[PDB]
Image: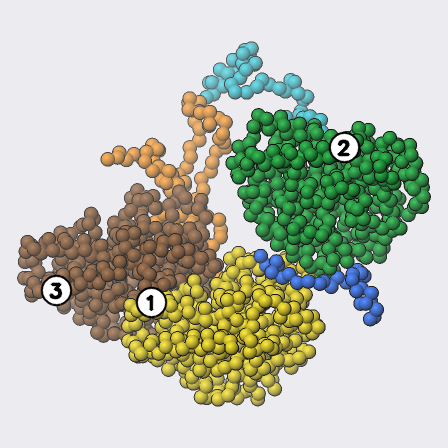
Chain colours: A orange, B blue, C brown, D green, E cyan, F yellow
Amino acid sequence: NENTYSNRTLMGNWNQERYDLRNIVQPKPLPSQFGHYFETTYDTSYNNKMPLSTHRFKREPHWFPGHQPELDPPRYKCTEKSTYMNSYS
Amino acid sequence: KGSLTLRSHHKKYSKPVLVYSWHRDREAF
Amino acid sequence: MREIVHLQAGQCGNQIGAKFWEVISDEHGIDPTGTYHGDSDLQLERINVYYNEATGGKYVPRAVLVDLEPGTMDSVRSGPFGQIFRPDNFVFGQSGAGNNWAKGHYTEGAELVDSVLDVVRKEAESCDCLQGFQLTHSLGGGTGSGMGTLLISKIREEYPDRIMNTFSVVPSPKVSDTVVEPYNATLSVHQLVENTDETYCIDNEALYDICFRTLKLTTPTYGDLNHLVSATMSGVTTCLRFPGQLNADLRKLAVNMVPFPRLHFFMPGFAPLTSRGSQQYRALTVPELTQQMFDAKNMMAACDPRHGRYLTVAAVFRGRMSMKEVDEQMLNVQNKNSSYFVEWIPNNVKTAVCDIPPRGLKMSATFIGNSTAIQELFKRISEQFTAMFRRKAFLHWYTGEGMDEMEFTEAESNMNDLVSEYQQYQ
Amino acid sequence: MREIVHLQAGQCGNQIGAKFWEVISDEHGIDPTGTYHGDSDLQLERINVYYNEATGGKYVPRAVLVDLEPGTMDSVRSGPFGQIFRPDNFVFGQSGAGNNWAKGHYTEGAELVDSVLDVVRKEAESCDCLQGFQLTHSLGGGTGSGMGTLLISKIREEYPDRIMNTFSVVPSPKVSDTVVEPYNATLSVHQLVENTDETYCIDNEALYDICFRTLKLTTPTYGDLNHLVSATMSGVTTCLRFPGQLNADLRKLAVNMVPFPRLHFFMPGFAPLTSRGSQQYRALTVPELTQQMFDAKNMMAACDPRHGRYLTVAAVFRGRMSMKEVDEQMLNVQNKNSSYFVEWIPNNVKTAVCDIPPRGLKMSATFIGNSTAIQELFKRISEQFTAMFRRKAFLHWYTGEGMDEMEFTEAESNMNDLVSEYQQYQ
Amino acid sequence: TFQQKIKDKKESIYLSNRRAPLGKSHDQAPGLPKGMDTTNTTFGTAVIK
Amino acid sequence: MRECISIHVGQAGVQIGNACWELYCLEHGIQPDGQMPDDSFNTFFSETGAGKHVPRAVFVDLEPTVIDEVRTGTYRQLFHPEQLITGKEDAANNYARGHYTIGKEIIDLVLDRIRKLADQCTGLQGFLVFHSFGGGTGSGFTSLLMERLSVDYGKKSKLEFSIYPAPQVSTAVVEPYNSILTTHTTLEHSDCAFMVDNEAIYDICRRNLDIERPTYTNLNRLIGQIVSSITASLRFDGALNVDLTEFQTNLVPYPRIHFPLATYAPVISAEKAYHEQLSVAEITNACFEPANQMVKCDPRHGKYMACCLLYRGDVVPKDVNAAIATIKTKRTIQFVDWCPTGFKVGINYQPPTVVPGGDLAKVQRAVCMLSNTTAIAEAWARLDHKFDLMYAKRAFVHWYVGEGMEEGEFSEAREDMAALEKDYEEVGVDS
Ligand SMILES: Nc1nc2c(ncn2[C@@H]2O[C@H](COP(=O)(O)OP(=O)(O)OP(=O)(O)O)[C@@H](O)[C@H]2O)c(=O)[nH]1
Ligand SMILES: Nc1nc2c(ncn2[C@@H]2O[C@H](COP(=O)(O)OP(=O)(O)O)[C@@H](O)[C@H]2O)c(=O)[nH]1
Ligand SMILES: Nc1nc2c(ncn2[C@@H]2O[C@H](COP(=O)(O)OP(=O)(O)O)[C@@H](O)[C@H]2O)c(=O)[nH]1
Ligand SMILES: [Mg+2]
């Protein structure tokens, strides 16, 4: 049917697994020696060469298996106030 | 819309602006 | 004030009740230890509905857990939230049913039910005004279906003027995991129909395609499947535990969804689920929630509503949301898809609104619908039952346990009369 | 008392009325907020002609702003005086005409016009005794010329016994900024001549030469050009708003300037404008205003009076003067330029004197002249029309929206006998 | 990469490398005045009102 | 010397009374604490030796979830602890559940405090009732409250403010059942009954207030604005005062004809208010316009019967005179031939107030219209049509007959509404 590889093969649905929280917090190695043989035009012209420090996230609740509220702005994280408490102060 | 429902006719203006019957309206003072 | 006694039977019921009590403990801010760790004060005003207060400022669920093999209660307790379940509430049996409706209903389950009634009646009189009972089990195995249907019959005569709700796990064609499951299904539905008020049909085929094409996962384990159905099990009683604008409890839903005593079968659904790739790119707004709810790929039953007609449907919303837009969307979906709704009754949609969404989310909804198309799965197990019964197969496990063949003809006669009653409204 | 309803359509019309209300507000002493800030008491007498007073002592203009694209009203509302217009006078659609006369007249401008008539009827009835209308637009394309003429054609049967002003922007030979300019202007002037009272031609070529030679400017932007013509726009209704010695409104003009119903095209002019480098050098006196106003370089149209004769001329003066200097001077220029005035009518001059000068000047004069030289624009655009129409170019964009071939021939035929009637007085 | 930088530092003498590097112009700092950043300054005659 | 008692039943009653009593506190300067920071507050706010002013209303509902928000919210110390009665189980969209089984248990608790509050006031005019037709509590519990208040107090007036079920949208399924089975009680045990419709307020808010997405919090502010404009003749001085008895004798010609309609104008936002003059002719023309009417009926299709005008603010009686004199010229507005004088006016000096965070603009003058017309029978006919095709298949009957009533109540309630419609059209036929 289909031969399942690892993540770094771009086979099947690799995009969602890259979007997953694990493959976000995995570190990105620095450019190394013999790296000039692996530069593309897009890499040289439309990209950034600053090293990236890893970001890590807390433990939030989940309500459906695809939920990921870690990558959200700090809004609606707390329990939201009722209509009476919003309007009548 | 909202404001177009309120048509009416005549309008007050004020006391320094003279309109029709401004003479009759100043005279009562 | 208004309390809910949760019932939990079978191996499937135990694996689905751990995740269900995980979500509620998450919803009200309860750690695995037991102490309330929350930030607001509205999470404690309605806490008695699911939790009993005790000394030390802790809360434990008022749920009973029933199974006939100790190999399952040992696993639900070793889970992430197994410490908070009461050690009294586990009631064991020596020999498992073995996917036989006969063992759990006349011989082995007939002895265990005396202790279960003692445990339930002790807890049920400890509250002040009980709202009703909710139950969750599986029809495909004799532990939860052979005994849980008997447990329904025992409680119904004890407490007649209450509401009885169930989340049944109906069988499926391709995920057929038991040879004799047509026997354990039709013998349960024959007794289930007369002694309950609300019934939801959760099927595993619909959960598998949802995780494949809507949420975009590769390995949808049972922890993921139980997490989807526990969203609607918590999303059905939002107005009981939280204030809103249009409060609607279980009985106020069952009045609007049950026009006849034999019409109490629903097809649940959950609105705001979206894959992680298009999570923050979508604009989560109530027309998008309505468009996702009414699609046939969001239902948790293996029935296509395009082949049937919606009798009554209900929608329970969460979060602050303006009611002009939701009322426009209910009116619009009624006017456009006019051929999919019956015409002998107007305004088939029930609207309820709660003002508190779940944590980390701003707007969610739950869909409950009584539809004519649910008769498809009843006919599909009717032809499998009749094909197996006409060859006199697999019956020496049934007639050898104090049973006749008459309750097989009576089960087929009642369920054929049930689907003949569903035929007329389409 | 006497009221003038202002209509404002087109991109050029919207940019020309924003500066028009800027000049009036500075003339009457109105802040951007909307409150009266004036040193004298004479400015508050005739404020009902242009302003509708609202509660709190705020004066809002009785002008309506209509266009098909929302991109210009955003610039108007973000302008310096944009907050004084009422927000419900902003009537606009969602799709532009895109330089097509048939778009703004037959397929897109025919829908918005049902609301435009409703808004202008709300303000035409609220006044006491309406004097007339005043429309500002351009012929450059079908957005403001396709529907500006249609608004004229809809109001004429609604209010037949009134007077209609129209400050139209005519095409020019060198600032031709539209390949289909002869199409959209000829099709408009066909529908414009028979149902209007006074029309003024204001082309960009004369404004460019005035700013570069008379005013000696290096950067004649559109803010500079709009202020030049708005001086004449506000200079034609001085006797309506301020007391004088020879009071003459728009109708007392129109009786004198219009001898025949098809001869109502005028030459605007402003006398006292002078560059800074010669402002101290030039003696500001009424022989200098009279000598300057009759020069061909001061005219607001690209026509030379040296190729035609003068039918009727009018001059409206602003400021405290004696009247016999100009009465001698216009008698003097009539005698010396005898070959340039038609001999079958004597006393071709009209005199209006107002006691209130403009802002920043001791005196002023505004020149309005019906001359025979205006056929040169009509000959120039008819020859461009024949060249484009003989090869049937650009006709699918017009015939594809409900326009027939013979309608263009009627537009050409009415153009040709207009100038055939015009030629016979040479 | 360091050895290739040594190689290109040695190779920078050449007329072809001075006239035409890959995807760029030649060095404009001899042409422009010293100390002027190119992407920040605005070239042309501004108009005066 | 004068007092009014308000009864708010159901979830709609307790939620439209919160915004209504919020406007009462702001009009007399009552902070949510319950004190001061003229003796016009004595009709609504009682007195205490410490200076505290407590209201004179009762809040009845079977849902404790919405009552408890009054306990939790800002107005906890102001509202009386016992004046707001709490149930245990909701009626669950059932007329039978709210009337026969549950409603008999809490009627004695409510009627005890009704008697206590009625003995507080020396002079009482009557009762104002805020409830909803389609609710289980607002229909089932009210149907016994009115039939027991009528025998406890004989000739006291009974004004009603009912949330009418909408022609197109609704939040319920058995709303045609709950609407029909309560009109038998309210036809005989009520004096006058105004109707408001939810989605009619939705379109007024969209096309006049220019708010795109309204919520019940501002619908209750509009309804609370109408009630304050009705009673403002009692509270404040004016050129001529109108009583609760005065317009209730001027709006009904017959005991069966006691259904007028409400209309409020001007309704506009803060940005649009300052650009046009709001004269008396400006605001009395909007009330006569069918677009501004807040019940989904067209008076153009119907015929006018009687009208009541309630003016507040800087209003002169002369320009009022020219307003009706202009209206009577128009043939678009049609009157019945037996009522040539169908106008009663009322004048109040005090302009309406505005709330912080509200939507309405600070307006100098306003008018409230209470018009009785025949066009309501258009809304009646389209509701019993929905009732009849529902009842033909005997839907939802076992929910009602299993709780204690019989099946003959459906037949007689439909027979009364058929005869009520026959009475409306016979009145509408001229000679
Ligand atoms: N205008 C307005 N209507 C409301 C409001 N709250 C509830 N309603 C109306 O009430 C109807 C539903 O009945 P509810 O009042 O909410 O509930 P109930 O009266 O307690 O009846 P049950 O549901 O059986 O308990 C809806 O159709 C609304 O029209 C409100 O705040 N404003
Ligand atoms: N969705 C879901 N299905 C389950 C779960 N656990 C068991 N099942 C289903 O239940 C069926 C077996 O039921 P069984 O354990 O024999 O029932 P019992 O004998 O009454 O305990 C299998 O076909 C499974 O698909 C669960 O956690 N989630
Ligand atoms: N004097 C002046 N002319 C303007 C201004 N804006 C645009 N125009 C003229 O409008 C002409 C183009 O007309 P156009 O906008 O296409 O007409 P429309 O499409 O109907 O709105 C050009 O020739 C400009 O000279 C302005 O601010 N002042
Ligand atoms: Mg209720």
Name the residue nearer the viewer: C79 or D181: D181
Circle 3 residue: C410
Mark nearer the viewer, 1 or 3: 1
Name the residue nearer the viewer: C19 or D405: D405
The chain identifier of the residue carrying mark 2 reads D
Point 30% across, 77% down: residue = F407
- Disc 3 is placed on an element classified as helix
Q: How far apart are marks 3 and 2 (CA)?
A: 110 Å
Check residue F389 in the rendering and tell me which mark sits there, or answer none.
1
The chain identifier of the residue carrying mark 3 reads C
Is D389 on the left-hand or right-hand side of C106?
Answer: right
Q: What's under tag 3, amino acid-wise?
A: Glu
Question: Residue A87: image x %, image y %?
Answer: 53, 64
Is C340 on the left-hand or right-hand side of C195?
Answer: right
Circle 2 residue: D424
Residues marked 1 and 3 touching at CB (< 8 Å):
no
Point 43% across, 52% down: residue = C287
Q: What's under tag 2, amino acid-wise?
A: Gln
Q: How far apart are marks 1 and 2 (CA)?
A: 82 Å
Q: What's under tag 1, amino acid-wise?
A: Leu
Question: Residue F21: image x %, image y %?
Answer: 55, 73
